[PDB]
Length: 49
Length: 127
Length: 93
Image (cartoon, rainbow over all chains, first blue to last red; front, side, top):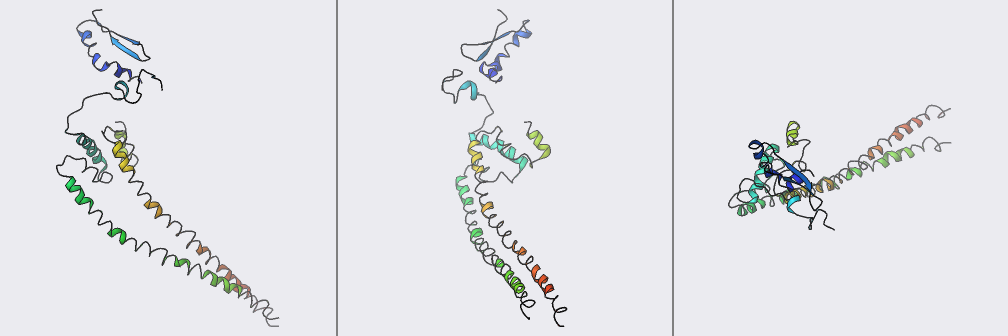
Protein backbone atom coordinates (compact mmCIF):
# COMPACT_ATOMS: atom_id res chain seq x y z
CA UNK A 1 0.00 0.00 0.00
CA UNK A 2 3.00 2.32 -0.28
CA UNK A 3 3.38 1.48 -3.96
CA UNK A 4 -0.25 2.49 -4.17
CA UNK A 5 0.65 6.16 -3.76
CA UNK A 6 3.59 5.89 -6.16
CA UNK A 7 1.03 4.90 -8.81
CA UNK A 8 -1.82 7.26 -7.90
CA UNK A 9 0.26 10.41 -8.06
CA UNK A 10 2.28 9.43 -11.17
CA UNK A 11 5.67 9.41 -9.55
CA UNK A 12 6.99 7.29 -12.42
CA UNK A 13 7.42 10.36 -14.65
CA UNK A 14 7.66 13.20 -12.15
CA UNK A 15 10.81 11.69 -10.72
CA UNK A 16 12.51 12.70 -13.98
CA UNK A 17 11.29 16.26 -13.48
CA UNK A 18 12.91 16.54 -10.07
CA UNK A 19 16.13 15.16 -11.54
CA UNK A 20 16.39 17.74 -14.31
CA UNK A 21 16.12 20.59 -11.77
CA UNK A 22 18.71 18.81 -9.64
CA UNK A 23 21.66 18.93 -12.03
CA UNK A 24 20.96 22.18 -13.89
CA UNK A 25 19.66 24.18 -10.94
CA UNK A 26 20.80 23.51 -7.42
CA UNK A 27 17.93 21.98 -5.48
CA UNK A 28 15.05 19.59 -6.03
CA UNK A 29 11.95 19.60 -3.86
CA UNK A 30 8.58 17.93 -3.33
CA UNK A 31 5.63 18.16 -0.95
CA UNK A 32 3.64 15.14 0.24
CA UNK A 33 0.18 15.75 1.66
CA UNK A 34 -3.33 14.40 1.82
CA UNK A 35 -6.04 15.76 -0.47
CA UNK A 36 -9.80 16.19 -0.03
CA UNK A 37 -10.36 12.42 0.14
CA UNK A 38 -8.50 10.11 2.49
CA UNK A 39 -5.73 9.33 0.08
CA UNK A 40 -2.23 10.87 0.00
CA UNK A 41 -0.66 12.78 -2.86
CA UNK A 42 2.87 13.91 -3.67
CA UNK A 43 3.28 17.09 -5.72
CA UNK A 44 6.64 18.23 -7.07
CA UNK A 45 7.34 21.89 -6.37
CA UNK A 46 9.36 23.75 -8.99
CA UNK A 47 12.72 25.38 -8.32
CA UNK A 48 11.46 28.79 -9.46
CA UNK A 49 9.19 28.98 -6.40
CA UNK B 1 -21.46 -0.14 0.47
CA UNK B 2 -20.28 3.44 0.88
CA UNK B 3 -17.46 4.95 -1.19
CA UNK B 4 -14.46 4.40 1.05
CA UNK B 5 -11.63 6.00 -0.91
CA UNK B 6 -13.91 7.91 -3.25
CA UNK B 7 -14.24 4.83 -5.46
CA UNK B 8 -17.86 4.50 -6.48
CA UNK B 9 -17.57 1.05 -8.11
CA UNK B 10 -15.11 -0.82 -5.82
CA UNK B 11 -14.51 -3.41 -8.56
CA UNK B 12 -12.31 -2.01 -11.38
CA UNK B 13 -10.84 1.51 -11.29
CA UNK B 14 -7.76 3.09 -12.86
CA UNK B 15 -5.63 3.90 -9.81
CA UNK B 16 -5.94 0.75 -7.73
CA UNK B 17 -6.14 -2.31 -9.84
CA UNK B 18 -5.59 -1.70 -13.55
CA UNK B 19 -2.27 0.20 -14.00
CA UNK B 20 -2.06 0.73 -17.78
CA UNK B 21 1.46 0.08 -19.09
CA UNK B 22 3.07 -0.71 -22.44
CA UNK B 23 4.59 -4.04 -23.53
CA UNK B 24 6.23 -5.28 -26.79
CA UNK B 25 4.14 -6.02 -29.83
CA UNK B 26 2.29 -9.19 -30.87
CA UNK B 27 -0.50 -10.04 -33.31
CA UNK B 28 -3.25 -11.26 -30.98
CA UNK B 29 -3.50 -11.97 -27.26
CA UNK B 30 -3.30 -15.72 -27.85
CA UNK B 31 0.22 -15.37 -29.25
CA UNK B 32 1.42 -13.35 -26.25
CA UNK B 33 -0.12 -16.09 -24.10
CA UNK B 34 1.88 -18.62 -26.13
CA UNK B 35 5.29 -17.05 -25.50
CA UNK B 36 5.27 -17.25 -21.68
CA UNK B 37 4.09 -20.87 -21.80
CA UNK B 38 6.74 -22.50 -24.01
CA UNK B 39 9.36 -20.58 -22.04
CA UNK B 40 7.82 -22.12 -18.92
CA UNK B 41 7.20 -25.52 -20.54
CA UNK B 42 10.84 -25.80 -21.57
CA UNK B 43 12.06 -25.96 -17.97
CA UNK B 44 9.59 -28.69 -16.98
CA UNK B 45 9.20 -30.55 -20.25
CA UNK B 46 6.66 -32.52 -22.27
CA UNK B 47 5.20 -34.20 -19.19
CA UNK B 48 2.71 -31.58 -17.97
CA UNK B 49 2.34 -29.24 -20.97
CA UNK B 50 0.71 -31.50 -23.59
CA UNK B 51 -1.00 -30.97 -26.94
CA UNK B 52 -4.36 -29.10 -27.10
CA UNK B 53 -2.75 -26.67 -24.62
CA UNK B 54 0.28 -25.61 -26.68
CA UNK B 55 -0.96 -26.37 -30.22
CA UNK B 56 -4.34 -24.71 -29.66
CA UNK B 57 -3.13 -21.25 -28.64
CA UNK B 58 -0.44 -21.19 -31.34
CA UNK B 59 0.12 -19.01 -34.41
CA UNK B 60 -0.57 -21.77 -37.03
CA UNK B 61 -2.87 -21.01 -40.01
CA UNK B 62 -5.12 -24.07 -40.29
CA UNK B 63 -5.54 -25.80 -36.95
CA UNK B 64 -9.30 -26.25 -36.53
CA UNK B 65 -9.15 -28.60 -39.53
CA UNK B 66 -6.21 -30.33 -37.83
CA UNK B 67 -7.13 -30.45 -34.15
CA UNK B 68 -10.27 -32.48 -34.95
CA UNK B 69 -8.46 -35.09 -37.06
CA UNK B 70 -6.19 -35.82 -34.08
CA UNK B 71 -8.83 -35.70 -31.34
CA UNK B 72 -10.71 -38.47 -33.15
CA UNK B 73 -7.72 -40.82 -33.07
CA UNK B 74 -7.55 -40.55 -29.27
CA UNK B 75 -11.23 -41.51 -29.12
CA UNK B 76 -11.50 -44.48 -31.48
CA UNK B 77 -8.43 -45.84 -29.68
CA UNK B 78 -9.93 -45.26 -26.23
CA UNK B 79 -12.81 -47.51 -27.30
CA UNK B 80 -10.25 -50.26 -27.80
CA UNK B 81 -8.58 -49.73 -24.41
CA UNK B 82 -11.98 -49.79 -22.67
CA UNK B 83 -13.68 -52.74 -24.37
CA UNK B 84 -10.46 -54.71 -23.88
CA UNK B 85 -10.24 -53.54 -20.26
CA UNK B 86 -13.84 -54.20 -19.24
CA UNK B 87 -13.35 -57.87 -20.12
CA UNK B 88 -10.23 -58.09 -17.94
CA UNK B 89 -11.24 -56.07 -14.89
CA UNK B 90 -14.42 -58.15 -14.49
CA UNK B 91 -12.62 -61.48 -14.97
CA UNK B 92 -9.49 -60.82 -12.90
CA UNK B 93 -11.77 -59.93 -9.94
CA UNK B 94 -15.24 -60.89 -8.60
CA UNK B 95 -14.83 -64.05 -10.70
CA UNK B 96 -11.72 -66.31 -10.47
CA UNK B 97 -10.46 -64.06 -7.63
CA UNK B 98 -13.46 -63.87 -5.28
CA UNK B 99 -13.53 -67.67 -5.56
CA UNK B 100 -10.28 -67.75 -3.61
CA UNK B 101 -12.64 -66.67 -0.83
CA UNK B 102 -14.72 -69.75 -1.66
CA UNK B 103 -12.03 -72.45 -1.63
CA UNK B 104 -9.75 -71.01 1.07
CA UNK B 105 -12.40 -69.48 3.32
CA UNK B 106 -14.50 -72.62 2.78
CA UNK B 107 -11.86 -75.26 3.47
CA UNK B 108 -11.52 -73.35 6.75
CA UNK B 109 -14.59 -75.32 7.86
CA UNK B 110 -13.07 -78.64 6.81
CA UNK B 111 -9.97 -78.35 8.99
CA UNK B 112 -12.26 -77.05 11.74
CA UNK B 113 -14.78 -79.89 11.56
CA UNK B 114 -12.02 -82.52 11.70
CA UNK B 115 -11.21 -81.05 15.12
CA UNK B 116 -14.73 -81.57 16.49
CA UNK B 117 -14.73 -85.09 15.02
CA UNK B 118 -11.39 -85.50 16.77
CA UNK B 119 -13.00 -84.50 20.07
CA UNK B 120 -15.07 -87.68 19.78
CA UNK B 121 -12.55 -90.63 19.57
CA UNK B 122 -10.89 -89.77 22.90
CA UNK B 123 -13.75 -89.15 25.35
CA UNK B 124 -17.34 -90.45 25.06
CA UNK B 125 -16.14 -93.07 22.58
CA UNK B 126 -15.33 -96.14 24.72
CA UNK B 127 -16.39 -96.46 28.36
CA UNK C 1 11.47 -14.09 -9.73
CA UNK C 2 12.88 -15.33 -6.40
CA UNK C 3 10.98 -18.60 -6.72
CA UNK C 4 12.14 -19.88 -10.13
CA UNK C 5 15.67 -18.88 -9.13
CA UNK C 6 15.16 -21.02 -6.03
CA UNK C 7 13.22 -23.76 -7.87
CA UNK C 8 16.03 -24.17 -10.40
CA UNK C 9 18.47 -25.45 -7.78
CA UNK C 10 16.04 -28.03 -6.39
CA UNK C 11 14.02 -28.87 -9.48
CA UNK C 12 10.53 -29.90 -10.56
CA UNK C 13 10.03 -32.18 -7.56
CA UNK C 14 8.85 -29.72 -4.89
CA UNK C 15 7.89 -26.62 -6.91
CA UNK C 16 4.91 -27.86 -8.97
CA UNK C 17 2.21 -26.25 -11.09
CA UNK C 18 -0.45 -24.02 -9.42
CA UNK C 19 2.48 -22.57 -7.43
CA UNK C 20 4.64 -21.35 -10.34
CA UNK C 21 2.00 -20.96 -13.07
CA UNK C 22 -0.45 -19.13 -10.81
CA UNK C 23 1.79 -16.25 -9.74
CA UNK C 24 3.17 -15.78 -13.26
CA UNK C 25 2.98 -12.92 -15.76
CA UNK C 26 0.74 -14.75 -18.33
CA UNK C 27 -2.30 -12.94 -19.82
CA UNK C 28 -5.10 -15.52 -19.71
CA UNK C 29 -4.57 -18.04 -16.93
CA UNK C 30 -7.88 -18.13 -15.05
CA UNK C 31 -9.42 -19.57 -18.22
CA UNK C 32 -6.51 -22.04 -18.33
CA UNK C 33 -5.95 -23.05 -14.71
CA UNK C 34 -9.52 -24.40 -14.48
CA UNK C 35 -9.28 -26.53 -17.63
CA UNK C 36 -6.27 -28.31 -16.13
CA UNK C 37 -7.55 -28.63 -12.56
CA UNK C 38 -10.54 -30.56 -13.90
CA UNK C 39 -8.35 -33.18 -15.57
CA UNK C 40 -6.67 -33.98 -12.24
CA UNK C 41 -10.13 -34.50 -10.73
CA UNK C 42 -11.93 -36.66 -13.28
CA UNK C 43 -8.79 -38.82 -13.28
CA UNK C 44 -8.68 -39.03 -9.48
CA UNK C 45 -12.17 -40.54 -9.64
CA UNK C 46 -10.67 -43.34 -11.73
CA UNK C 47 -7.76 -43.95 -9.35
CA UNK C 48 -10.15 -44.08 -6.37
CA UNK C 49 -12.98 -46.23 -7.73
CA UNK C 50 -10.33 -48.63 -9.07
CA UNK C 51 -8.48 -48.53 -5.75
CA UNK C 52 -11.46 -49.01 -3.43
CA UNK C 53 -12.17 -52.33 -5.15
CA UNK C 54 -8.59 -53.51 -4.60
CA UNK C 55 -7.87 -52.29 -1.08
CA UNK C 56 -11.03 -54.01 0.22
CA UNK C 57 -10.33 -57.27 -1.64
CA UNK C 58 -6.59 -57.57 -1.02
CA UNK C 59 -7.29 -57.27 2.74
CA UNK C 60 -10.10 -58.14 5.21
CA UNK C 61 -11.24 -60.63 2.55
CA UNK C 62 -8.86 -63.22 0.98
CA UNK C 63 -6.14 -61.99 3.39
CA UNK C 64 -7.88 -62.10 6.78
CA UNK C 65 -8.89 -65.65 5.81
CA UNK C 66 -5.25 -66.63 6.12
CA UNK C 67 -6.05 -66.09 9.80
CA UNK C 68 -8.92 -68.55 9.34
CA UNK C 69 -7.09 -71.46 7.68
CA UNK C 70 -3.69 -71.09 9.37
CA UNK C 71 -4.86 -69.93 12.79
CA UNK C 72 -7.64 -72.53 12.59
CA UNK C 73 -5.59 -75.56 11.54
CA UNK C 74 -3.60 -74.67 14.67
CA UNK C 75 -6.36 -76.49 16.57
CA UNK C 76 -6.14 -79.55 14.32
CA UNK C 77 -2.46 -80.23 14.98
CA UNK C 78 -3.16 -79.47 18.65
CA UNK C 79 -6.12 -81.84 19.00
CA UNK C 80 -4.18 -84.72 17.42
CA UNK C 81 -1.81 -84.34 20.37
CA UNK C 82 -4.55 -84.80 22.99
CA UNK C 83 -5.88 -87.76 20.99
CA UNK C 84 -2.32 -89.02 21.02
CA UNK C 85 -2.26 -88.77 24.82
CA UNK C 86 -4.93 -91.49 24.81
CA UNK C 87 -3.40 -94.55 22.96
CA UNK C 88 -0.45 -94.83 25.36
CA UNK C 89 -1.92 -94.57 28.87
CA UNK C 90 -5.54 -95.31 29.89
CA UNK C 91 -6.01 -97.27 26.66
CA UNK C 92 -5.12 -100.88 27.60
CA UNK C 93 -4.74 -102.06 31.19
